[PDB]
Length: 228
Ligand SMILES: [Zn+2]
Ligand SMILES: [Zn+2]
Image (cartoon, rainbow, N blue to C red; front, side, top):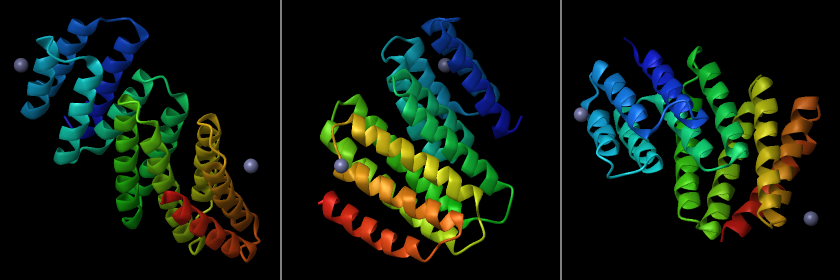
């Protein structure tokens, strides 16, 4: 079939594995069969390694995401990222990925193609965040999240000059989750920058978009200082 149903089938298989309905060998066999049915041999060879016991579920998910990036499958990328951030116990990152998927789905049904690139770059940043979390590199996670907040700031700046309103609400929700994550990581300046960007977005959405700009410059300057 189409690449839309492949992502749904793979997501259902991984969800069954995570909920405990099936085991590792059953998951490997089912996902390999799904990949072979759609003609994707490169993903099938990766799943063969999990079937052979060489690698684990998380490493296989990472390799599958890297291969899907090269192949250009987007819904598969979102499914794989959600599965990765569910294997590592982080509900907040899963919520961020869910909101990002909603924005991508809204963007693909219209002519907006500039936001697709932004969502791709932020997917790259989130993948790097997951890789740093897997290595327990807590210093790199903060820098990657700062880059993610800068990308969200770029998106909100682009959206304000347009008529989009639900984009502002989704970005505000994402920024609030990011600020909560920063607070739980024992940081306050980056959390303050995230909340400043969120406040600017909310002020622009409310109707007062003149006070939003000074907040935007203040927040971006602070983020650039804290990235170094
Ligand atoms: Zn095989
Ligand atoms: Zn404070």
